[PDB]
Image 1 (cartoon, rainbow, N blue to C red):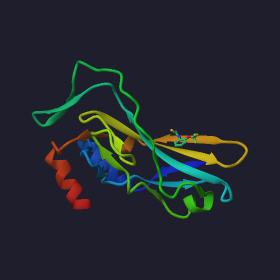
Image 2: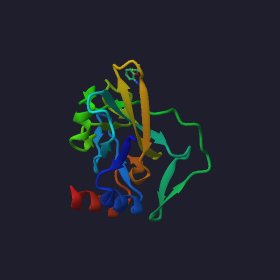
Image 3: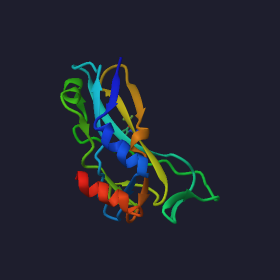
Length: 171
Ligand SMILES: NC(=S)Nc1ccccc1OC(F)(F)F
């Protein structure tokens, strides 16, 4: 059975208990913490691509009101995010299983862009999700996994200074 684990879940949970925030810029900003996934149970000899996307966790615009994030009462259906391909893709199962798969180079933006960068809507809440795509073989297959621990709100600047301090402390 294909097993997918989050690496450093301890640390993600410290961000989640404050409500995590990720900066978006026009040029794109790398994530901290980095999503790192432990994968076992692949066919070491089969070929896979690792894809990352961001599900809109709800339809609401969020605002930091007097020290607390609060959703609005004007939600709308959210266009789904673009998919980032892990730059090691495509690769053998053995490649993916020898170390945590680290999405260190994805950049989060707020603007339609040259490509690579993933566009999010500022002040929306997102749940990172991966797709493991068995490629090249006769039988294509997809295993998907969500990481609730890694939920965040996309922001143009940090609102909660406890997040700012945690980001620096652990970077
Ligand atoms: N989920 C997506 S958008 N996958 C994808 C991305 C880039 C090229 C091809 C892709 O899918 C295909 F291989 F199944 F066609």
